[PDB]
Image 1 (cartoon, rainbow, N blue to C red):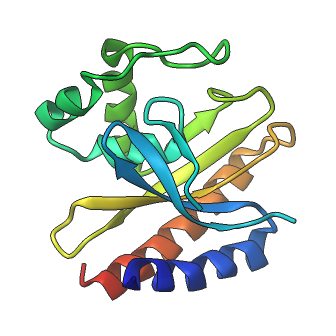
Image 2 (image 1 turned 120 degrees about the vertical axis):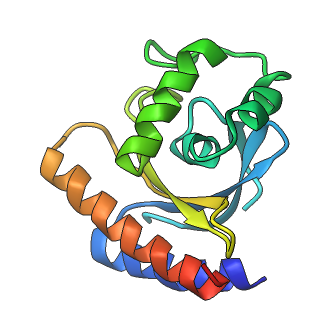
Length: 164
């Protein structure tokens, strides 16, 4: 597929620029599926509500489609920070749409942080999320903003190559 071929190039570029773990994820019913990865030094499945990619796959969607997708989900509290109801998640999705990126701030695993941005198809629907990992510590608003800016560049190229 063309999405993975374009993504592969831009993900290798982010890995080059950042040395971080880069993922490409897509919606599989009521979970995310990792479809590509470039490692720090693919088929894995994860919750929609605790992943940065999950948040971006939902945030631009019709909010009735969202509540539909999330109907079947059994929320599980992984960590202190995990969002564990639809009612708690919908306001988070508002912020994701507003700011243009989604995050997982130790919501799946202590010590793990991820930041993600939407990848659009030719119609403006989010078809994948493109993310960057993180060990949590050296937090810099500056690192976050630089990471978001480079994700957006990468995603816009992938989307353009999709016909967006």
